[PDB]
Image 1 (spheres, rainbow, N blue to C red):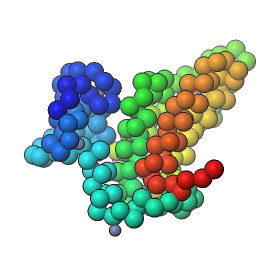
Image 2 (image 1 turned 120 degrees about the vertical axis):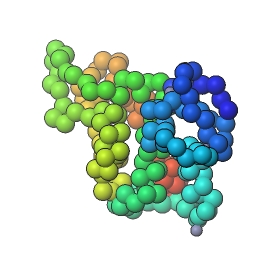
Image 3 (image 1 turned 30 degrees about the vertical axis):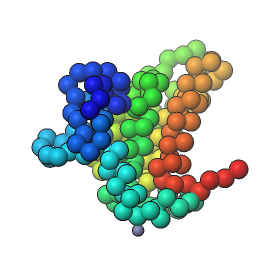
Image 4 (image 1 turned 120 degrees about the horizontal axis):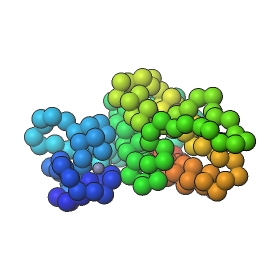
Length: 178
Ligand SMILES: [Zn+2]
Ligand SMILES: [Zn+2]
Ligand SMILES: [Zn+2]
């Protein structure tokens, strides 16, 4: 197994996957690493198993169909993995915790949003459809663009949104387009 956390790239108290060489901090894995379960398989292994069981699940889909799916166990898992993929980028630190807004010439957003809040919402099964999760994720970056306006700090929102969007298209097998 790896000697660093797959998500945050630091050593510490790590839990090791039994089916691949990844390791995790307890609250870096999503969902949080399970108390018992020997063997234990991480979210990367669980996602690979879904595709292996149903190879046709990788054929191209329309985004509009994906968004309307109900959050059954497999879609819940895919959203947890997509959230994890955003936490795996170090620039996710800017969007993890509750923001505040006091900048000359800007007003804060109507509905603030952040990664930890989305993490809690997923854990408490508050989203009924994939659309709920995706809308909150996109809102994080949209609020950031709007608030920071012409400051070059707006680019962090662009960069982290690109990681989200790429991973969304991969995990949910969105039909490739020009
Ligand atoms: Zn970690
Ligand atoms: Zn694994
Ligand atoms: Zn199948």
